[PDB]
Image (cartoon, rainbow over all chains, first blue to last red; front, side, top):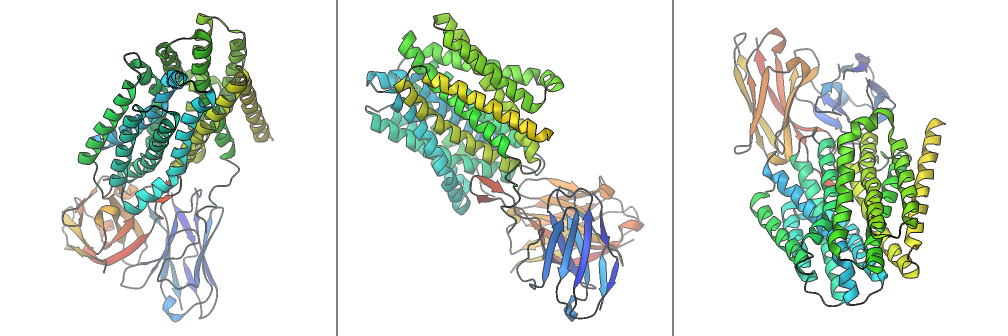
Length: 105
Length: 370
Length: 128
């Protein structure tokens, strides 16, 4: 189950609205997760469901689903958000990550 | 798999055997005291109410404390209930024993289901639910048979068997079991409705007929529980074997809803024939052929539920068990009430309910076509 | 609190072997599953393997089906990834994460814990 994440790169300024879509071909279950990774460190959990929010994560992040398109929304951006955000679905025992959205602030 | 799964399956097979144990020996139990059919149904009905009421509380206790302790506590309570039921003298002490057994069953079942979910791999979950349904149905069929087997030597001994088997299961569980906003909106409340209603009507009709057959035989044929249980379990094994061996041909030319609609049609016409049936061998044969349809309805219903669920097979199993208990309590009280008011009113209710299931399946098919 | 530490990595001859291990601490190993992901230099992540301690079920990715063997011993709370054949595509920074799998009882039915890779240890590096 391959998933396409669009776009690949996304430049942005501070305090804007940024959205990233990772589309799953077989989308029947909302087992979508998103990870933020900084250069030279390990990715940290950002969303662990369709629209949930893990503890210790800023409230500005949010997720949503529409049929097959999974949207991550950053309502307000800060310099900290300089990182790469990946999509992951684990509906089955197999796990497949996305391609990556390296934002450039 | 390991024997830890065998013990867990036994913990449910024995529970449902105890569920079905009362029906064969019930007529002598409540006729030597001379009790109206209302209480005869009310015994099993109160068992089912206890099970369903304690099911969520039992699951909560299993989650908050630990599955092993809840399982052994429930086996101990079930063994105590089965030992006490055979040392009863009046209606109250028997209803209390049935209630305690029901609460033990309803607080064991969630614990065993959770343990099986925690031990089984993520891919053998639909299959495990299939074995769960198969074991539950086998216990439902086989309870009365174990009752009637040694209901012959004495009328307290089958519950001695039940208590001894509960103690044995408890001692295996002690030495073998070891410990390791979109939540509710996922169900659309418009897809599971048809299988829910269908399993409800199936369980209701089956429990009602199982309750009514013993009363009818006792009040008209004046016979012993032995061949009553023999006929019930023979119909059960006939239907189960028929379906499990010829489902390859059944699935070839029939769909699911068509199968479980023509099943109700066959059951209702055979029950209409049962109205005409008034002879010993005639009533025996007609009950034997009636039970086949009720027994073969269930596998199609659980297959439909599994197909509908897809990935939420735990939810499907929980809903199926809850609504099976719903039918198993709604049936017996009304069956006893009508048997009190008239000897064929339960039969008329059964055929009407079968026709209601028929029209429900018909409207589901029409909605699917539209 | 909860931390994960990994050992191994370094220079590997092509086709050689290396035992990549993850040391667990702070969480219940038998109520969680340890998974391994791979990060190629300048590329995106990709799940490699996963083992569930509460059930003994192991899963491998299609590109890696039948070449890396995963295991986890509960006694020392360790997670093992055995490498039997390495190549150019296998060079990466390998991370080790924990996947929480514990059934919670909603009334009348058990529901699994939501899928998540909560705790990540600083991954080691495997070259060549």
